Amino acid sequence: DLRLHLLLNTSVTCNDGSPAGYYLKESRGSRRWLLFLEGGWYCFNRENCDSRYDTMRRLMSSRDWPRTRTGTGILSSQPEENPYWWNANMVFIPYCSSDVWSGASSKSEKNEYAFMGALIIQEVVRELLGRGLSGAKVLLLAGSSAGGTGVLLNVDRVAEQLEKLGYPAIQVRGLADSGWFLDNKQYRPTEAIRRGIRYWNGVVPERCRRQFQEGEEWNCFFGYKVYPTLRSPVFVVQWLFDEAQLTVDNVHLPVQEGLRLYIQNLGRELRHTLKDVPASFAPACLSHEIIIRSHWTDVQVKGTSLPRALHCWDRSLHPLKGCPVHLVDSCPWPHCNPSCPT
Ligand SMILES: O=C1CN(C(=O)COc2ccccc2)CCN1
Ligand SMILES: *[C@@H]1O[C@H](CO)[C@@H](O)[C@H](O)[C@H]1NC(C)=O
Picture 1 (spheres, rainbow, N blue to C red):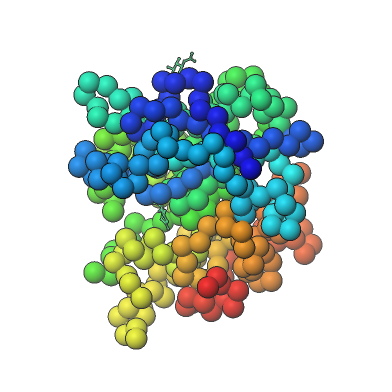
Picture 2 (cartoon, rainbow, N blue to C red):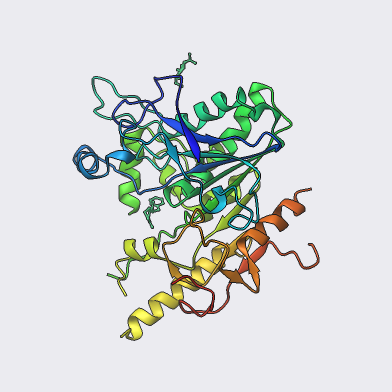
């Protein structure tokens, strides 16, 4: 069980002004720290956020959060469930800012909601330094879905924050799960992100911002465009036929030729964007499943599981015989990999 701590700086808030926070389980015999960002879409205007507040309020407020949560998958402390990092210090950061972890805007007389995702990450890091993070050797910033995109937007800022605070020995790395999307043509989204950035006062990594310039920061929410600008090591996990990608593409699964070609082209394009990503795990599956699920160990690419690939990545940051880190399926249709989830 991970225990809840509400932020001591109560000006760093969820959407409705309640304090943000984190769940923590310490492991005093370990110098490894895993900070995981939750996902759950976003909202981009007053009316859309009001609807989310009625029926997804835990994603907008801490008022009803439980005092504990169970760590599962990569957050589990059991070796059988988590062969990778079972002995690590574990942190789960709830997503209560509805801004893909990009915002830096407080509630005020002109803003009904606060969008503070980027500041929540910074304040969690600062408060953890007094609870053992000051002695860390590795800080892995991980996340799923909107949290996976959040890793790409925030990993370099965490590295810069720790350097400026006086902790240059902590190696900051990222793990982005299910947050690598394509701005492709639909079978039958970029505008919502553009509007969101203005509504949230959203921030993007500085090198990417300088490439795309004013008004075009939305480009930095797409992994294939932001990843080449990042300095921290980042491991990318992405299903080739991600269900959220298909949803935004208006695809809902007797498949005729037009849809067959569309699905095959999508897998080929995703595979192409990962060609120059040396640490990656991309199975040919139709799924919405994420790395905090208990059975995350089951899927394999070319005979190698994700916990193994992550271990090989750790070794590479000290190619390796029998320990691969670039694992992208080449077969062209959902479930052509026999180990895909059901
Ligand atoms: O499959 C899912 C989808 N979810 C997401 O957050 C979608 O991912 C993103 C990533 C970036 C921006 C918007 C959405 C959570 C619920 N289960
Ligand atoms: C609390 O956080 C806000 C936003 O980052 C910051 O302006 C303020 O200085 C912080 N307060 C303290 C006491 O650190």
